[PDB]
Length: 386
Ligand SMILES: Nc1nc2c(ncn2[C@@H]2O[C@H](COP(=O)(O)OP(=O)(O)O)[C@@H](O)[C@H]2O)c(=O)[nH]1
Ligand SMILES: [Mg+2]
Image 1 (cartoon, rainbow, N blue to C red):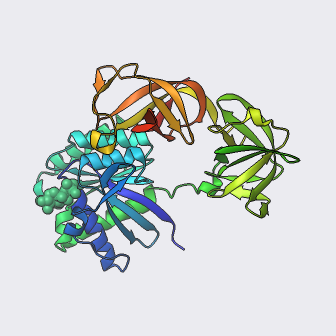
Image 2 (image 1 turned 90 degrees about the horizontal axis):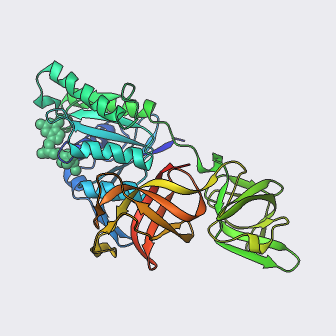
Image 3 (image 1 turned 90 degrees about the vertical axis):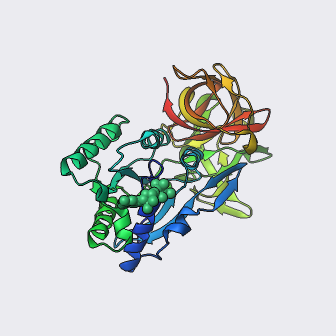
């Protein structure tokens, strides 16, 4: 029945992200929509290790009248960096927590910048610790500050809901505290839209393997990432070489002929007229017009540390690694932003990349940076250039 939304608390350390998360689960538990997870349980977040990288993330779930939420919260700034860039945590929206007594702090800025770079589409703000601020005008001035900062990263600062409260008082069962948590959750319900179903997006399928079979022609295999491909419809073959257009004449799985393949399906797709030598791993099938090939882009990247399997020395301007996009490596040259001389292991930064061959790409596409077949970085395309 209820639509599902993924969110998380972001913001500077000590501003009350965890207290707020705990208060949400408490106040919703009390309305019959969650198990109360106490502060210590959320704060002592399990470390999860995946692809060399350890991230501490608390996962909590709750529901309002309208919606079901999965909510993430992390102890440290570095967990946010890694989750948001690697996509180990996805957010359809974020609750930005700012201490009203401190105002925005450097990770308040960094998390907003990250939200922009990795495509978090909406922010709601909880201005926390108002029990520490007795002056209403000071409160308004902090709020105005948060709005200016949000707008400076192109979020709609004038329209973003900002709820003022004390997460700590809510935890202590103060009624005014609790009402703020409920106003926060109403704003989340109404402002953060439920994301588009993968099935409704334009068809896209990364090609993993290509086959030329006697009396069948050219077959490509992979997983449909999004949308639906139907026998008889046209598809573009995008990336690496000039775009080509053809007709899907078949979709199949082991011992199963299909009329179509949808998001999540691992299928073989028969391409009418297409020569095996014109298709390769690293291209995508797509809805015609829906995605273009590019060589040049900006990305937010996280560079692994030595302990994660990464480099143990910095790189510099013109570094020339591989970029693993979906299924294949393409070499590219890295340009660093003005004011950045070097990128250390464990840093995150925005870079410009120029690949030696085009890839079907769009904002939000993730990739790995590799050196000699070893992953040294994780990125997400933040802007297409030209
Ligand atoms: N006075 C006050 N303190 C708070 C409030 N919310 C959190 N704190 C305290 O600020 C500290 C940091 O809170 P925490 O939720 O761990 O911050 P996080 O680092 O953002 O997750 C803890 O001592 C909290 O109890 C609040 O509304 N008022
Ligand atoms: Mg915390």
